[PDB]
Length: 425
DNA sequence: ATTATGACGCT
Ligand SMILES: [Mn+2]
Ligand SMILES: [Mn+2]
Image (cartoon, rainbow, N blue to C red):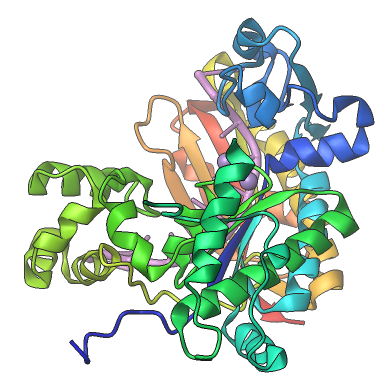
């Protein structure tokens, strides 16, 4: 009872830009704003592959990983913006720079963990304590939370429901106890409203956010009310929320492990996990996953918000699917040089912006007909930022997968070059 | 033939 810690020590938010690549292109091209539109890579094969979809387009059924020509069959008015192409490949530079704008704003409020190009986690515990002291017992007004949903409320028109739920939550709030977890989440959400307002002011970009006591719940909350809304998931709301949450919806259970949880244990929803002892879960899924599942199904996760705004690796990848697979020495050399040239550009920019050099070069390839996504992965030294040297070294390091007797066999369906092992410069 | 990345765990 008194000693069963409930993992309410922290306030953690997950901020995620709504259809990020689409918004970047819509800021740049006003003709796309408030339209069904999507961002694509390439244009020859089936119109190109969609990697980002506006909410207007989603309402027609357009999804990521779908061909533009098929999307156009669901949504004939769909507008398309194309990723930049450089040295024969997709170049995501515009979005990395837009991402950095956003990250730098978020960093003004608290320490952030860049979790992907369009989303970051925030540790708000210190910010909330400071702010709670600043109120000096003053109660929290609904006006401070204009886009916040309280998950699980109301109990017992869309905006009408939102406001009822918020009213229930705020009426039930104990503003004098500077140590109540629910008060702390609430103040955290006020700060997140401010962060999202500053992001929109200063970039034009809208985002959603989740506010809870840990990373997994913050992330799950962020998705409950998209777009341009934020959702507070309290400790108390976990039992009902999880009672019908499919296991696959939780971060890291979306794949094979989640499928084996479902199959082995004979269950469907996160909440069912509570009925198993910790040892039972560790037995089925190993000691780490077992402890983690035993606490997660109760709303408790201890993974910290890492103070890391910048990517830990810088990578360059191109698939050569179908009949485009690389089959000669000349071909493999030229594409390794194109990849190495983009990598050199990004690395030099990184060294100047962020005072660090990479020291290790990772070369990965896929060969045709190989089941694996990485047919091979080998590392060598990365000593100077020179594309000719990096491409030569990647060759040097992969060339003994050629089984020919100036040809290349098995032909390569993927090249990948990744700079890693960063050291302060 | 949806692709381009990137974190992290296992061994
Ligand atoms: Mn997003
Ligand atoms: Mn998405």
